[PDB]
Image (cartoon, rainbow over all chains, first blue to last red; front, side, top):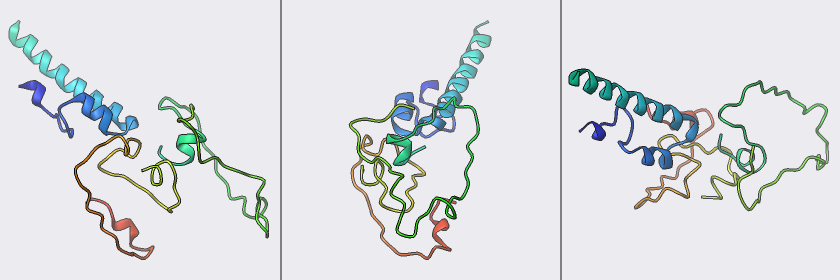
Length: 49
Length: 50
Length: 49
């Protein structure tokens, strides 16, 4: 279900963001998605530990 | 950016570092009959690299 | 959209919710074009929020 999260963006698919939005701020949007999914993975890792 | 020059004439990469300086040259570079010495491009087969 | 994106015979073109670079690349169902005349003092009001 974490793959369905937009994390405040306009879409949950990074391909859609890359092919839909201007790269100078699409880099920031992809960075935000990356750090959101990284935080989710860190939460899962701590719970697993 | 996105425009006629920002696509086919002059591009700036996302990691560009520096300054851009602009000044009004209407008192010097303009002509009463029009200055045709400066030209710009509008047609190209593909996007011009920065 | 080359007459709007690649070429600019018009004074100002701006895209807020969509990438202006990939206007020919984005594919949509239909467009509702609203045509009207606004004086130069109030043309800044055409923006969300």
